Image (cartoon, rainbow, N blue to C red; front, side, top):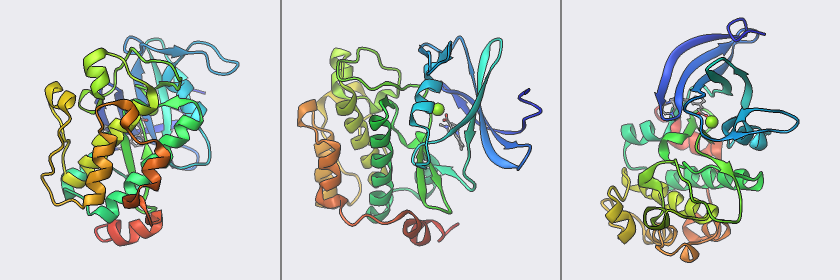
Amino acid sequence: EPLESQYQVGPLLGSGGFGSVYSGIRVSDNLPVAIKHVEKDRISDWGELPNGTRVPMEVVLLKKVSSGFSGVIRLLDWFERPDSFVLILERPEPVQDLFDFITERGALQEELARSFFWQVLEAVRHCHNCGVLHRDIKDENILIDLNRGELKLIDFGSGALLKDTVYTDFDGTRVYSPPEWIRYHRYHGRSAAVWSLGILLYDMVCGDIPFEHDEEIIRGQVFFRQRVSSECQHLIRWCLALRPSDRPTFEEIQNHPWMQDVLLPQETAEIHLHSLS
Ligand SMILES: CN1CCCN(c2cncc(-c3cccc(/C=C/C(=O)O)c3)n2)CC1
Ligand SMILES: [Mg+2]
């Protein structure tokens, strides 16, 4: 029953606004896991969860998207403590987040960016279909299962239930938030999500984020610092359309020509990941 008699804690993987996550192993089968600690004082949103009670919104969101689909991390279990909650999440091995992967390898070839991007679209779409809005889509929040070549969306600590009405609260990453939020402190789930997908695609093909200051976000002028195909630039600028309604739907993004003939996960890994893995 105790958390200690359950898992064997390992080294700290990282910490921040989300909390502190450690590498871990489940004593029983040595199944690799991650142990995330979050203080109750940090937690702002709470949920009830089916036939349950007091629980952080993060847990509610995680369980809602839980399933066989490997595009989003799986909550394996959780525990409540006097001042914190502990989340036991799955952990692919080897693994590396998109931020480190790009920091190390730099701007990705378009074929690779296509595969990776396509996989987050499927993951985000999955969340939406399950009534969950992530709100913090970014390189750091996407894990790369190097052997399988499959990406995983993580950290639902900024998410919320998907809704068709306005959002007047945001606590994700500033440099990924849309111009509606910066200017009017209001946005709609899917539109905002598409904007951050635009920032992410740009990050993938250019090695860095397109905007830094609020003034750049509001103006939305995209400058390509690396050689990027015309199709890709078009998609990117379409997602980064100043007016929300001018942004493509997920269907339009995935039907976009630059998005065609995506590589399969294993293919991707064999051609791009095993080369160094
Ligand atoms: C966002 N991350 C910032 C960068 C360092 N960091 C890392 C690094 N490598 C693997 C994982 C890792 C492995 C398995 C599950 C998870 C899940 C995290 C979550 O759902 O919050 C994370 N997390 C902690 C959080
Ligand atoms: Mg999470």
